[PDB]
Each structure stands twice: as structure tokens, then as C-alpha cells.
Image (cartoon, rainbow over all chains, first blue to last red; front, side, top):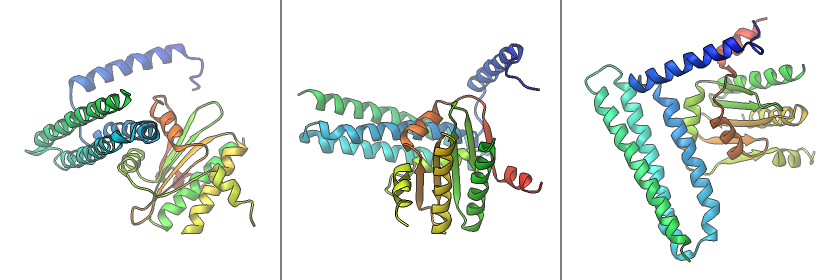
Length: 128
Length: 73
Length: 70
């Protein structure tokens, strides 16, 4: 059954995908399934830090180490997020499943905050 | 053609290495038409998540390094 | 081990140039020491992977062993 020329298949698959997508946003969130989600967080973080690594030398020296610290803060933020994800998986169906879901969301909040500060610190270094 | 043969031989030797030396291996292959072929000894996502956590130097090779190495035997 | 590692990278390079393919290779050894290879650049290949949402051939250890017995 070659599907290279089946538009019916394409639209049915597209329809099924929107339903699964809708159900995953309404109905959370089996741990173990967290792993690809946190991976994409770590990947998008890597390209950002590598972007900054090649960008820092074009910025004034008086801002180098204020930027390098916000980098390391984001690294700890990621390893911190990974720690909570593994704890939520260990308690898939226990009293503390909800407890570590909340702590992941706290580490997610900190990633957004400390990345925005990394942006604000770089925006300040540009003002020359 | 011989792509399927050489691709599978790559996945086979990676698997042999993962068991012989107790390793975690991920393999990502994009072809000329940008289709994805991937192999992982365990779970692709776990290996890739474990990859991002690694904030640390290590060995990294590329086609340029390999071509130079094979030009001295 | 070190020979098996370079032999695998040497073979990944051969597939890269003989069949015009971008290849990433990620290896953790038994002590979680990292070694890697990218035909062009690891940053761009992984970037290309992140934006790939489409279906693809994905294989694991069980797929290799099954195929090996024919």
C-alpha cells in the first residue's frame, strides 16, 4: 500500500493528528512521554548558547562575564528541569505524581525568566 | 540501491559496538532528498536528552578530520 | 574499542560522500564519556532534526537483530 499519491490518506492523517493534538493539550500528560518534550527544550537551549558563544567576542569586554553567568544559570536550569522530570516518572501513579509535575512547571518558569534576562543583558551590551 | 545496503551496514556495526563495549549510540541520516533515517541502540530521545545535558568538551570529528586522517598511512 | 569507534566514524563518512548524506553520530561510552561525529556540522544537522515533524524510518536494536536472521 504505497501512499505517495493518496490525498485521502493525507487528509485523514491530518484530521487524526489535529484530534490527537487537541486531546494532548486538554488531557495531560503521561510521564515517560515527557522525555521528547524536555529534549526539545534542551536542544533549543543548545543552539542559543552556541549562538551566544560566537557572539560574545563582538561585544565589549565590560559585559563578557555578566553574560557568561546567565549562560551557566540556564545550564543549571536545564539540569534542574531534567531532575524533576525523572522524579515525576518515578512516581507515575502515586501520591507525588502531582507534586513533581508542579516542580517541573516551576523549573520551566525559571527557564523563561533566566533566558529573558540573558536577552536583556545582551541588549544592554549592544548599547554602545 | 547500494544506499540501503551501506546504510544498514552502518546501523549493524553501531549495534555491534553498543553491545561489545556497552555504549549508547544515536545515528541520524538525512539523504539527498532530505528524508530521515535514524537508529538508536536504546531510545532516541533519551540519548538526545542526555546529549544536551552534556555541557562539556569532548572529542568531536567531522568529514574534514576524517579525510585528513586517511591521508597519512 | 577505540578501533571500533574510528571504524564506525570512518564508515559513516563513507556513506556521507558516496551517497550524499548528512550524518550525525553520538556515542556515550561505558563511563558516559562523549564522542561525536558530524559529516558537515553537528549544530546544523541537529537543527535540521528538530524541525523534522514528518514520518521516517526509525530503527532500534530489536529491528537489527530481527533483520540479521535472514
